[PDB]
Amino acid sequence: RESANLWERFCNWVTSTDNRLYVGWFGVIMIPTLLAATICFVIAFIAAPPVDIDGIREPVSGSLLYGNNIITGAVVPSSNAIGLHFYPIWEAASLDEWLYNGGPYQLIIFHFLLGASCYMGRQWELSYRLGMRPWICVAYSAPLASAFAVFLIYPIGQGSFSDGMPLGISGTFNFMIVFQAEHNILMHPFHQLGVAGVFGGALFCAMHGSLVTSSLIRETTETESYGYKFGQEEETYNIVAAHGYFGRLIFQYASFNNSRSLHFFLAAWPVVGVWFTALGISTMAFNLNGFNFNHSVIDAKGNVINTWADIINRANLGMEVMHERNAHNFPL
Amino acid sequence: IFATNRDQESSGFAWWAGNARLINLSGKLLGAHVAHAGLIVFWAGAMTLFELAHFIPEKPMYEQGLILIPHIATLGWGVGPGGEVVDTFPFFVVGVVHLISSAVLGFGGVYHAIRGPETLEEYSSFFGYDWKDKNKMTTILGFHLIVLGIGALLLVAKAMFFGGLYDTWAPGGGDVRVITNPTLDPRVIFGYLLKSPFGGEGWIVSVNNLEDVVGGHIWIGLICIAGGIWHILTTPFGWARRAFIWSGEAYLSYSLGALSMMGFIATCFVWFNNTVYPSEFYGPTGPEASQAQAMTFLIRDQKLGANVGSAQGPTGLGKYLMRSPTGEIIFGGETMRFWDFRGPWLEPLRGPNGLDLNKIKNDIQPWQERRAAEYMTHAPLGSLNSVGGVATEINSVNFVSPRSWLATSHFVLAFFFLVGHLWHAGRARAAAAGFEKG
Amino acid sequence: MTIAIGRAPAERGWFDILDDWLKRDRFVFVGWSGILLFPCAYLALGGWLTGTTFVTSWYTHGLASSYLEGCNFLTVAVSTPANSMGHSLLLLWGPEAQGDFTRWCQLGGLWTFIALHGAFGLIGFMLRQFEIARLVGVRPYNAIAFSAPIAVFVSVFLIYPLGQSSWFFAPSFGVAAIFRFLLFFQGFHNWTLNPFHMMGVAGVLGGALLCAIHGATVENTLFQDGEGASTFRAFNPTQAEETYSMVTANRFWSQIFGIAFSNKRWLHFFMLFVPVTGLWMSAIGVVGLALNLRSYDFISQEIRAAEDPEFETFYTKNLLLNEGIRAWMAPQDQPHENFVFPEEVLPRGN
Amino acid sequence: EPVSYPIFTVRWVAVHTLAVPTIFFLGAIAAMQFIQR
Amino acid sequence: RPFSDIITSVRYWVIHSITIPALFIAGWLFVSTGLAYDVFGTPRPDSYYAQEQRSIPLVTDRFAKQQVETFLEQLK
Amino acid sequence: GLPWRVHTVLINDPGRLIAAHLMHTALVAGWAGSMALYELATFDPSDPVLNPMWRQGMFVLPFMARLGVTGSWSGWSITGETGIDPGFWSFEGVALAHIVLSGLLFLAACWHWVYWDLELFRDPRTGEPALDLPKMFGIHLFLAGLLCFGFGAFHLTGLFGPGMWVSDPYGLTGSVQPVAPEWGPDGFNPYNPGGVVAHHIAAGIVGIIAGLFHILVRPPQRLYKALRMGNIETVLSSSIAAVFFAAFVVAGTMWYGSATTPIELFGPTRYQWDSSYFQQEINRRVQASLASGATLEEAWSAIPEKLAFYDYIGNNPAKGGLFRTGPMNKGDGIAQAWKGHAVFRNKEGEELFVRRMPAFFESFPVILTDKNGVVKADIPFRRAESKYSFEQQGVTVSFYGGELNGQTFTDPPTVKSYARKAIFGEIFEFDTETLNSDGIFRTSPRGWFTFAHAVFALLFFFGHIWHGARTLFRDVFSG
Amino acid sequence: ELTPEVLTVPLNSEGKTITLTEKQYLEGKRLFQYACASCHVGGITKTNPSLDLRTETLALATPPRDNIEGLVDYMKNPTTYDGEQEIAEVHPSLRSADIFPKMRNLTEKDLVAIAGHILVEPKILGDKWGGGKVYY
Ligand SMILES: [Fe+2]
Ligand SMILES: [Mn+2]
Ligand SMILES: [Mn+2]
Ligand SMILES: [Mn+2]
Ligand SMILES: [Mn+2]
């Protein structure tokens, strides 16, 4: 048949390209999945009916045509009522109901992931397709995680995509704030390591790129321118000088094998730093919040003496007290 | 040929990869694998006892960060109408058993990394792996599906032909036992197929019928024993054969994700399910908890005299009821969502369209109030320290919920192991081509 | 028409020329730069540890800020002087010296101490990279990257306060007291709406991004050469040839992401450009908030929103939170004034 | 050339000015841990 | 790298084994006594407030600040 | 750085670079006079008492003002115004004056580029030769100096007199006087103009001595080898760090200090308001009249009307930034006279005061406490279960003084709205349209000027840290 | 600090007082967190906010619950705020110790300490104990 014969053998060879173409195979899912969502997103964002994000009836509208600019939100999350149910675009005779119940959201989400997930899958094929070594693949396993958290985990943790980050600048800004008053995150190791991770990565990226160039030386131239120168041879930068300066600045440096180890160190520091933060949330989703150091006392009486962590609360409170009104009763 | 050993240079891998070395040396790994095993056995015992010790009776399990005990309970021990610590003895039992049952391993574990054939051749035993003999690989696995297989059955038996498998229904608690159912139908299969997861319905992670679980396992204990038998018999086939690569690490990867998945399934099954995870033992399951908050206030308020059915919240929805979407009714708020809840107490108040403004209006016995009041105050949530609750708140308690610790760790685990899978399967796929380278 | 010198080579006759040699030796690099870095750095690293475990805030804020008082790493902190004292370098001499060093501590000298000293220490370290970089005969591009962080540091610790009265609204050099600063900002200056920081974020988060691609790319692109099987950490740092290999990298991306530029001599610059840049940008950002020039009002929508009560954007919601934070957070925060917001305090619903 | 039997080494200077103090607190702190009021 | 001789010296052990605890204990005394307290002026649980009026004093103061502080401490 | 671118060329040259420079000059005076004309075809002479540059613022104006220029045809001033016237050659002129000289420069930049161429240178040686620098930085300083000096004696000090903007606290009076111061013173305090004038006279001469010297006594090999001296880069970063420094300070004094940053010609300063300044001056103003005869019423018123305005939040650079424008206008609206503060009283009239708005906040509530912090009445948010409701009133929202003296309102709203407005300075009557006016505060020159200059000053750091690099490091730049 | 007035509270409604010992104070905190904090954390009342443990509120209850004896009585035989109906089936107490297990292990001494905690805390925390000021 058509599907049949060498045709298949041929088809198969092309994707493989181888270277031649551119692619390849995984894409065969990635590609289409990602196109649906990219397309659904664009349209919803440019123009779409306010969504009943909350469990109630006060439609938010983060799209462009209904009174927005880029910073002001995107595609608001499904309804607090659909909660966890699977609300495609079939259920209900009218699509107009879909837009309202904030249905476009679930489309994007489910597809993006499933795609960026394939993207991680394909991300490695061309490895096993050019002699390459895997790993890079796991490097992308760090952001994918962070995305399942913010789109599958957290909701599956709390009973509804309704909560758990919306598309668009502000929507994030919401998500983010709300969530901190709900878990004191800032006081949770897993985020902390995420900051060291990310804050550091940049720090490090600065250096590698920095020292390299300062060498380369060678021268050549013158014045014028340168670158251229370258282629392878010969290399363009040639280590030694680099090391001859770095070492001289901080102290005597050592690792398994310079470049070969001076690059692994780059490849992991941020990756593991971010990793925990993917968990960190997945953690706080199934609900296990950050630290809570609210009361130290003057036990000479019991009157309570404050502490920089008390204020953190005061603020989280007036953040909790409003937020949603829706719520109613008782508480949460 | 000659005498074994060699940690590095020769071996390659370097330390912190002082395990890959055992990938080749059957015996050596045996105990690596044996010891470790016991190591869990150990833990098991170590903990139950470390659990019991710190265990006050009739003072709520979940209220005592008790991860283990509850398990035993479910099975059909330490019961009395709705957890009444009838018999903390069974707990001390499983304790020692493992703690001893471990040295037993420990010895015969440490016994393969230091003599014994190494182993170688051784014889037978031894182984091989796999390279040499893709068949024993098969026959061993299969010779295991029996073990894994038999296990199941033990459950069903305990449950029925033995002293029950406690059910948080009846009706309540208880337990029962049961018977089974399971066986049953299938429908057991229908549960998957359808369923888804988502929403509711859703798944499983729903399954309520203690019967269904019991009679269902039957199928599995059978299901897989069949496989362990059939597997031995032959070498795979020709697609299975061509489709998969074959190596310790490869197999590793293969079975490394085998867990991450189930792993997840785990976290969920707990945090959501409820039957397999009572609550008289564990926590009150977030969904349920956000729901007893209604019972208490519709109850508290209707106890002041506001007609529930017509009451209208700020939104203009249903402040009490409502319703759812479808319607139903239921509840609401915000408990709008977990209207998939379902479970004891809240059940009676039900009917066809759910929650009878009639029952609710007057047919809700005074124990549901307390129970529903308890839960929300506990639930879960927391913070750490723990405390618991818221954040803011403060102081006281402590203390945090058991129902969440369980579900907090596993994701972390399930997840990582997925890193594992890939990481450990893109390498296996690079050796299988000569890469590293060149 | 003299395009040349005054009198022959050297410097201050006997010494310098000599002194240079001494100060520039070869065991754990000292240097002139260090002659003014070390005192500071240490002097300033210490200061923080001291308060951390030994000094209180009470009189300046009213929070316990040391281990001794009962805090813990996170909760511990070296609080800011009281607003009562505004902008004084609060030298151990102005508001009386000899009497109480103790009181210097009380009022809050340990701050400026850490601020001003670290300030110079940061000046110091930049030089300790210029001294060295020049000696070894290598490019100062490491110092440009460092100008970035300093900027980030001069805006938030020196400028800002000079704007909004008195250091005090300057972070307190506290693990947890920084978070208050964070939130404080969110709710008060509405940082998010700030295109400027918004940028910064892009940089830092993106600098971390690049750091994990490259790194992963490298290790994954590597060669067999220098083989010995597993644990491939054998590249002769002696010199010669690429360890990884561009072409392969390039072909990969090209067939994957659709942009795989060559010229490591650009990949390592792009890696510098990002973070350095981003911090300068976001740095301007705060220099702005230093004069309360901020966001917190698109203006085009708070107007369109006072007519349409059925108007709702993730923008207005965040604007609500911002206000809840101010109302509740306040009076614990800054005793600078009397604040007693009766229970009609901006809650609503729960 | 440090390590090999001098003692007038600046390296020694720093190396300790961080050391002594720390130990001094590292204990100081373990001492506070015992406080009730 | 370098540093592994002295730490493995044995005589080193001698000199420090006598010096370190010596320090560890001095501080532990500087803390228990009160100097820690009286020098860094931080309040011992006993001294917060005065059981007859709160005003987390500033402071416021100052000065005149100090003079003000003094009175504050005194009255306490 | 590496790569780247360158331128250177210029350086040194020299020639051509000078073209590059001759041109960039022209662009500023082009702009320089040019701005003025914008400002000029929009400037509101109507009422200096309430619709000042401023408010318104101026910008540009302020300066023209302070240094001695205050008026044009229509024939108005300040211143015165018445018328014044014276112137004769003011505003109008200063502006044009720049358009001409900005053109000569251009043209000059022209034939100085076609001839290098022758121467330067030587022888020884032869051778161348880049030039010779040490002679330059010796001869230039000579002029600069002579110039600094001049300005001091012959201008500020008087005799060719158009001095500078002086004014006694709280504004009100004030003007250009010899212125013166011167110187021485001994007063170095930044406010006492005195300094302004002595500084320049001294610096000036100090300038001449230093310059002539620097141009008559060459640079040591060591100091000459030291700063790569002789290769422009170094000259640049050297001066950039100096603008970098000049800048920073300027930003500072425009935000706090004065006499080169005067109340009238440029915003009140947040600091005057933070300190509840003025109002204590108002209190003494009335209190004396109030009691001492016356018554019551017245015182117040016484116281112014001018002070009453220097309160009010719309004018505090805060706011814012961006916002823006205007301011200082689209926000507030146009300053239409004063309504006199009012004294909100209880059902008995316990004077009751209104808790001012911090200039840090935006969404601030009305508290209204007894003359000692006791909360005598504070407008609710959750009316249910809410006490201290305004029922007792504050109904004594009764005003005293200008355009509303003797005239109370018991109506709960007017009483209440009035508080909401009282919540931040003396309450004024505003013109909303005619500029549309959004209703939201907007900073001022004092606020902007001090926003740019600090940012600019901070970006030039990366300027120093970088160019100076090329200086000390040229050989490797290729590397 | 744990001064006399702080530990001395009304024993009964007749005006008799009792000065709790420091060990009764500590035992009270322990016991209160054990059997009451799940719902009365910080002096509030969860399942029903208006009925807090603030001393004034207790004083206007029927019968007076602003004394040791009265609270003791409450833990044994709880009533609605007007004292017109006993409510042990909803409120933990010695009478309802079969459904409220944590009450099974409380001794008369225990009940006295718990009662002492309720009356003392507000003298230490001030409003924070009532409707949670620092907490709300
Ligand atoms: Fe690199
Ligand atoms: Mn929500
Ligand atoms: Mn919520
Ligand atoms: Mn919720
Ligand atoms: Mn929520």
Image: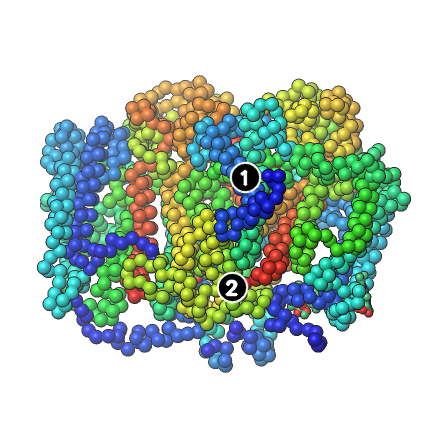
Spatial separation of the CA atoms under disc 1 and disc 2: 35 Å
Task: Please provide percent x and percent y for residue A151.
Answer: 58, 40
Say left or right for G25 vs E19.
right
Q: Does the residue labelled 2 lie within 8 Å of ligand 1?
A: no
Pick the front one: B11 or F418: B11
User: Does mark 2 fall on the same chain as mark 1?
Assistant: no
**Mark 1 neighbour class, 10 Å CA radius: few under 14, some 14 to 19, many 20 or more:** few
Mark drawn on residue C223:
2
The image quadrant that residue C240 belongs to is bottom left
Give the SS element for disc 2: loop
Residue A314 visible? The answer is no
Q: Looking at the picture, how far across and down is residue F15, in whole percent?
A: 15, 56
**Amino acid under disc 1:** Pro
Q: What residue type is labelled 2?
A: Phe
Q: Residue at the location (76% across, 29% down)?
A: B347
Number of the label disc, if any, that sits on residue F63 = none
Above or below C289: residue A84: above
Q: Is residue A58 visible?
A: yes
The chain containing the residue under callout 1 comes to: A
Q: Relative to C140, is F120 on the left or the right?
A: left
Q: How many labels does the image show?
A: 2
Residue at x 46%, y 55% (from the top left corner): C250
Question: Which residue occupies 60% across, 74% down?
Answer: E17
Q: Mark 1 points at which residue?
A: A32
Most distant residue in the bottom direction:
D5
In the image, G28 versus C199, the foreground residue is C199
